[PDB]
Length: 154
Ligand code: HEM
Image: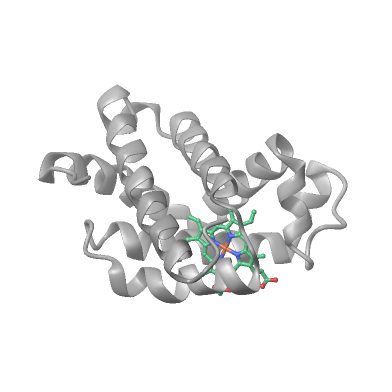
């Protein structure tokens, strides 16, 4: 699949807002992920013991994790589809070290869309959401192809 420049512009325009507060968006997204799909929390040894949203909101480790995910994702989106180099080390660590099934990448995709929708209604209408979904699907498709080459494709 391939996105048009118009679709990339919609994605990057809302992302510019996310970047005004990377830590805040990272927390919201991870908390949304962990509450909607608790099984995912088990993958994070440094934060799996957190029982409530209040504990999550106060966690310094959770906030650092959020910044890391959004910074790596942002670097990928800014490549506008030319992200093969950025995807390799990422696919290897999630396939071989962490063992993250594609299904969980779909779950975090949902959390991202949910949060942008809440915090940026004016820059996240239907067209912009369609573009973001398309960009995240592109990301998932390429990652899963890499998973298979690496022997996981879980
Ligand atoms: C847009 C999605 C994702 C991006 C861009 C991403 C990115 C990263 C990055 C940059 C790291 C740092 C170094 C490394 O590769 O180990 C990392 C670590 C990790 N990722 Fe992700 N990740 C994503 C989704 C997920 C999801 C959905 C899960 C689990 C449900 C996950 C679990 C992990 C774990 C377990 C680690 C290591 C945490 C630790 O240091 O203890 N990742 N990820």
